[PDB]
Image 1: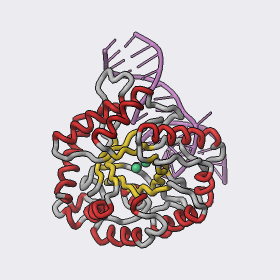
Image 2 (image 1 turned 30 degrees about the vertical axis):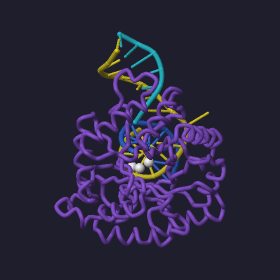
Image 3 (image 1 turned 135 degrees about the horizontal axis):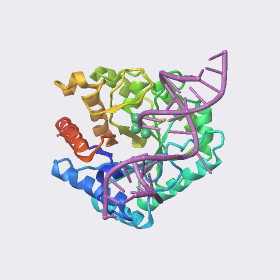
Length: 298
DNA sequence: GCAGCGTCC
DNA sequence: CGACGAG
DNA sequence: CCTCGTCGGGGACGCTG
Ligand SMILES: [Zn+2]
Ligand SMILES: [Zn+2]
Ligand SMILES: [Zn+2]
């Protein structure tokens, strides 16, 4: 089946006095929370650096314990890159080198990939900045669907996605994946509210498997507290935002349930990205989302 | 007409 | 979002 | 030991003078 999980923040999950092993400690509590509510988490997402500063956060003892934690529970963990990881920026010599550090760190601790945000630029400039990166065996760079309004390239329609990854394949750049953030393609103007709306988009995705195979596809399962076409990114819990709140009564006619079926049939990783002000709010929200997910799964 | 910000990811 | 200091 | 203020080597958004 699918590998379902959530983003694990340091502030809302780590114990006080976690000292040198705060990321692994947070994941430990996050795995405990999964067993309590009867949804064994198979995936997770963390920041090993930043995300707003070009500094590595994870420390040595954390790197050793994180590898043991990942192996023990067999977790599919992905690292989200910092917001400064723009390899196609003008002065990007300092930027690309920092991404090289993260990719090396990911392989040391057994993290499966690194998420980078696509820019609102041409695919030629995208592949150019990507070529400046030497691959790291076992770590996939997942290019995430961005969100904007006024720019030509949003990488949310299958035409723009197919164009990008074919230029990737012609350049012969290995270890590149796709991260589909549902809240972002919605913000970029892709109606995925109904089952058919998502099914048509997801069918066009499978129709270009020869350029981006589902083995290199991961998902951010996020509802959006914004209008379709906003360019503005406001995450919300599943069936509690503008995309799927109208389908809370019949969740198997929503667009999300079609995403769950594709994630299931391809064993893709799926990460919920929820931010709330405090631990208990976040846990109440995720318990609702993962029990609903368990309904669509089991 | 444009340059500089503040806010959010 | 997370490290780091003030208190 | 704590809590809380601060501030980021990018960028999209909308706003302001
Ligand atoms: Zn992201
Ligand atoms: Zn995302
Ligand atoms: Zn987002």
